[PDB]
Image (tube, rainbow, N blue to C red; front, side, top):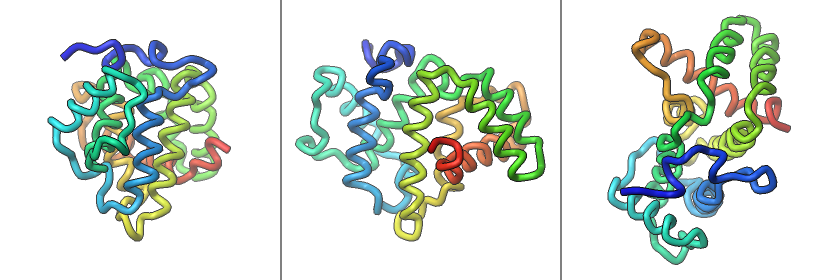
Amino acid sequence: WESNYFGVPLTTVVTPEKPIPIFIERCIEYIEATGLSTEGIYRVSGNKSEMESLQRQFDQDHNLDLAEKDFTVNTVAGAMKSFFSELPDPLVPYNMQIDLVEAHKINDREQKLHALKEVLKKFPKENHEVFKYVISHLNKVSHNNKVNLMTSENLSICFWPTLMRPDFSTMDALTATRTYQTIIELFIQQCPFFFY
């Protein structure tokens, strides 16, 4: 199917005054109100038909109310990720990724985090805002890990491919895996240091 909202550049669906895509707001706000206790949220994949549906229905009118529509929490979670994997360019731009990976080389933890926050300063503002929003949301989901089982480590495992889209004819898949996973885990766990 075709869309004016999904699969289009990030700037097309955000303004500097309302920087978070409305679809992302709906899903995250609904997931926070409905799914913070669901085991494996974001890790479990949902009905692909139900997501395509949710996206299509939202495409029709942007005031869609997920409450009045009886969607699985996993369906809304998966549909939220889908928006990001459908973006023409990954939320975390490739150029920033290079710098992110470099900073990560620094072994001392405090040093490493400063290095990382430095790259974080160079993000395009449109992305930095959405990244901030998503990451804090994930930080919150992680605060209920005893119940929902999704520690910050787990959450990056579900998210780093989606947010970064690494090209694996450019690095060893296993090593690139540990590297991206940890980077996102740090952004999630050290959310306050990176974003407060």
